[PDB]
Image (cartoon, rainbow over all chains, first blue to last red; front, side, top):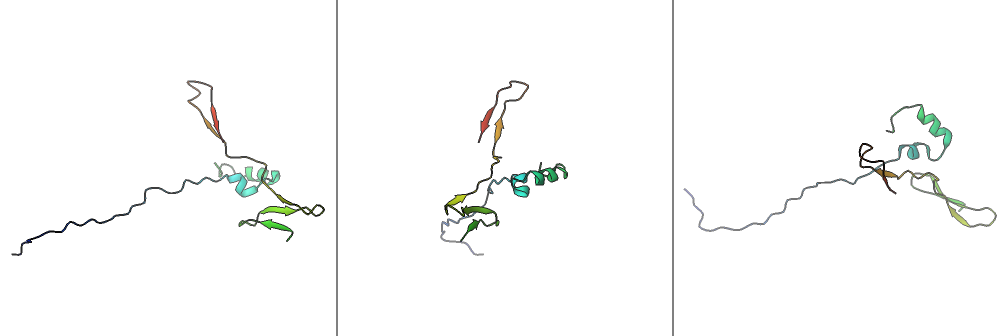
Length: 50
Length: 50
């Protein structure tokens, strides 16, 4: 058998992500900017932005 | 240089042909509004976060 006659105390680092960046997108402003008729066309696609 | 654009290629600033001043263009549609409500069941009051 082999038995230890001494010890070492080791500190080791573990790294874990917990969060992302909370991002939001204004669907209408992304797709159509400030064009009224582009927005009207976008209404034809329903609830995709929602 | 007559006008400037952002990463998306959106025109962000222009030069007035006559005065030759630089004007930034910002969308006239604020879509960063949130409404805090305790519920229509309990009250009709609200708060607004811009």
